[PDB]
Image: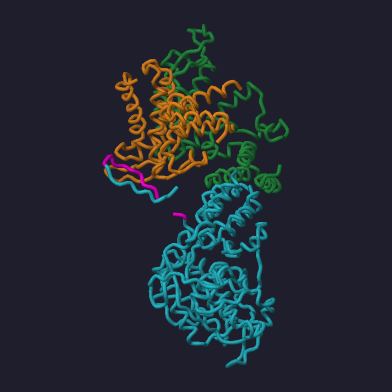
Chain colours: A orange, B green, C cyan
Amino acid sequence: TESQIPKMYEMIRDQMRTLASTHKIPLNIDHNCEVIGSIIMAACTNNRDLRPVDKYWFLMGPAGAEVMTEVEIDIQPQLQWAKGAVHDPKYKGQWYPFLALLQISNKTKDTILWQKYPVTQELEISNSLEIYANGHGIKDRLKNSRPRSVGPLVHLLHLKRLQENSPAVNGIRKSIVGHLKRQCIGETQKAMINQFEMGRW
Amino acid sequence: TESQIPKMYEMIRDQMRTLASTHKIPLNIDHNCEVIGSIIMAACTNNRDLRPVDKYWFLMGPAGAEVMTEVEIDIQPQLQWAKGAVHDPKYKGQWYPFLALLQISNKTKDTILWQKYPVTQELEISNSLEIYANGHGIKDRLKNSRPRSVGPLVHLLHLKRLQENSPAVNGIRKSIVGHLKRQCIGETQKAMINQFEMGRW
Amino acid sequence: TESQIPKMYEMIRDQMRTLASTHKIPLNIDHNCEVIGSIIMAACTNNRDLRPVDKYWFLMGPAGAEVMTEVEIDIQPQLQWAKGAVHDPKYKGQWYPFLALLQISNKTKDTILWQKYPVTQELEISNSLEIYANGHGIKDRLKNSRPRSVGPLVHLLHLKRLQENSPAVNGIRKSIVGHLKRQCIGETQKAMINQFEMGRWESLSTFAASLLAIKPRIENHFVLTYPLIANCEDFAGATLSDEWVFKAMEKISNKKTLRVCGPDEKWISFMNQIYIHSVFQTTGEDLGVLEWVFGGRFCQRKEFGRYCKKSQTKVIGLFTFQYEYWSKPLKSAPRSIEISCRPSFKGKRPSYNNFTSSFYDQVREECQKYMDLKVEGTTCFYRKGGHVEVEFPGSAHCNTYLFG
C-alpha cells in the first residue's frame, strides 16, 4: 500500500514543475498549482477530458507582480507519461488507487470556496450530510479503484443513480452496496442499505 | 506581405532536411517528402497532433532501392523551432498567414489522390463545387489568419457548422460571413450569403 | 452608489423647470409635471423616441384656471444635457444605474390608473402576480443597468421573449438569467428557473404558484417622481438608504402647492396614496402596514372605476401626505430562511438540546418553507425623525392590497 508511495510522489511532482516552468508559470502561487495540477490529474485518469493545448487562468508576474491572464500551455509530454503510468508496473497497480485519493483531495478547495451540496440534494437528504458525501465528481474507474475513500452518500447517489439510470449494471451496484455496508458499519444501517438496493428510499 | 517570404522558405527546407537526414530518409522521394512534410506542417500549427517519436510510411533504400516501411523519427528538434516562430516578431505577424497557404497546398494533393467532396456534400450542393471549397480541414486559426485563401464553401460550411454548434463566436461568425462576403463579389451572392448566416439554406 | 445621489437630483430638476417655464407651463399640476418629466426622462436613455419639438397634454391656466390643451415645447435645450450625462465622469458611471431607477419609478401612475398585466399575461401565469414583474417597458440599456430593480418576471418575460425572439443572445441572457437567480433566492426555484432557461415552462404556472409562496428579493431605491422633484428644493442629504427621502417629500406635502389630476374629485385620496405608492415602491406592500406607516387608509383600485382619458383628466385637489415610519430599501432577500448542539469536546459538560423532537414536491416543499415562515424583511422598520428600530403593532388592513 505505502511501499510505492515514496518513489510514487517523485514523478508526480516532476510533471507539475515541467509544465509550469515551460511557459514561465511561477509555482509560488497557489492558483498556478491548483489549475496546473487539475490538468495533470485529468491527464492521469481522464485522458479524454483535458485538452492537449489550452489557455487557463494563472498568475503571471515576476516577484509579486502576478496578475490574472491566460497563457497557452502544452500538456502533451505529461499525457504520454500519465497514460503509460496507468498500467505502469512500477506502481504495483497503485496508480488509480492513489489517483482516486489524489482527485478527491485536490477538488476539496473548490467545494469549500463555493459551498455546494450536490450529492445530498440529489439524494433528497439533509445538507449537513456532505461530510459523508466524499468522492463526488471523480472518475468512475477511480471510484472503483478507491471506493472506500468515496463516501457512502456518493455511493448511495451512485446507488440511486444506478437505480435511476447489460450484465455490467449489477457489478457496479454490488461493489457500491458492499462498500456502502463496509463504510456504514451500522448493522441497522447495513440492512436499510440493503433495502436501498431494491430501490426503496 | 512578401518581405518575410524569403526567410521562411530557407529554414523550412533546413528543417525539411534536418528531420529527413536525421533518420536517413532521402529527399528525392515525394512520399518521403510528403510524409515528412506532413509531419513538418503538423509541428507548424497543430503542434499536439503529431507524436514526438512516431513511425510513418517512408521509402527507405539507397540509390533507387527504396521499399515501403515504417520508420520511427524524432521530431522534437523540429517541434521546438516551430513553436518559437508562432509569435516571433521577426515575421511581423505573418507566420500564421504564411502557414495557412502551406497547409492548403500540401493537403490538396492528398485530396487529388483520393477524390472526395466533404464540404459540398455537407452543404447539400453539387459535388462539382469543391473547387470553391478550397481550404477545408485547415486550422481555424489559419482559417482566420488567411480566410481569403480558404474557399467560401468551407467558410459557408463553417458558417453552417457554427450554426449547427460565447462572445468569441462572433469573431468566428462575422469574420466567416465576412470572408464569404469578401470572397463572393456577386451583388446577389453577397446578400444571399447573409441569409445563410440567418440559418436558411 | 449613494455618493453621487446628492448631486444627481439637482440637475434632474434643472431641466424639469426650464422646459416648462420657457412656455409658461405651471409646475403645480401633476399632469403637467408627469408629461414633462416623461419627456425629460425619454431623452435620458431612449434619446431617439422623443421629438425635439412636439405637442403634449398639460394644464394651461393661471391660479386654478387650468384647462387641458396641447402646448408645443422646445425640448432641444433639454436634449443636449441628457446625452452628455451618459458618459459624464461626474456620475462615476452611475448614470445608467440612476436612470434605471428613475425610469422604473416614474411609470407607476399610468399602470395603477390603467390596470394592465403585460408581463404575467405574456408569461401565461396568474394576473395577481404582476407584483413580481417590476421593471417592464424600460430600455434594455437601463434593464442591464439595474437589472436587480427589474423584477424577475420581466427578466423571465425577457427570458421568455429571449427564447421566443444568434448565440450573442447568451450575453443578454446571462444578465437575464443571473439576475433571475439573484432575485429569486429559491433553491428549488433557481434550478427550476434553470428549467425556464432553455424553455421548460411546464413549471411556469408552478413558478406563479411558487411566487405566491417564495417571494424574490426586489432591490429598491427611494427616488422621487416628476411632480415632487420639481417641488423639492433640498437635495443636500439626498441618499438612497436613509430617512432623507421620507422627510424631504413630507415638506412638499406641507407646502400644499402641487395638484393632482383625475376623472373626478373622489380620486383625491387615491392619488394622494399613489404618491405614497410610487415614491417608496409600496404598491404591493400590505395596506395595513401602509395605513400604519403613513397614518392613513389606502383606497384600493376596486373602489374606483376606469381612469378617464389623459385628455379629459382634470385637477381635483391638492397633494397631501403624512407618515410616521420608514426603513432602508430592500437590498437582500426579504423572506430569508437564514438549534442542535454538536459536541466537539471530549471533556464533560451538560449537553443542551433546544429541540424537543417529485421535483414539483420539492418546489412545493420550498413553497411551504415560506408559508411556514413568520418573519420577513432583513433588519427592521424605523420611525419618522430618525433610524430608531420600530416593530409591528399590527393592522386590520392586513391581507388587503391596492389590487388585492
| Residue at far top of view | B65
Is residue C338 located in the magenta-colored stretch of the structure?
A: yes
**Residues shaded magenta:** C337-347
Against A147, is C385 above or below? below
Q: Observer-nearest residue: A115 or A192?
A: A192
Is residue C277 located in the magenta-colored stretch of the structure?
A: no
Q: Is residue B40 left or right of residue A91?
A: right
Residue at 59% over, 70% down: C401
Residue C116 shows in this picture: yes
| Total number of numbered discs in the rendering | 0
Q: Horizontal and vertical percent for residue C267?
A: 62, 82
> Splitting the image into 4 quarters, where does residue C122 fall?
bottom right
Against B104, is C357 above or below? below
Against C3, is C10 above or below? below
Q: Is residue B191 left or right of residue C189?
A: right
Q: Horizontal and vertical percent for residue B106?
A: 55, 26
Residue A51 shows in this picture: no
Q: Is residue A138 left or right of residue B156?
A: left
Q: Main secondary structure of the magenta part?
A: loop
Against A146, is B94 above or below? below
Q: Observer-nearest residue: C383 or C329?
A: C383
Q: Observer-nearest residue: B87 or A107?
A: A107
Residue at 59% over, 20% down: A167
Q: Horizontal and vertical percent for residue B4?
A: 45, 36
Residue at 39% over, 43% down: A112
> Splitting the image into 4 quarters, where does residue C50 fall?
bottom right
Q: Horizontal and vertical percent for residue C3?
A: 39, 68
Q: Observer-nearest residue: C332 or C372?
A: C372
- The C terminus of chain B sits in image quarter: top right
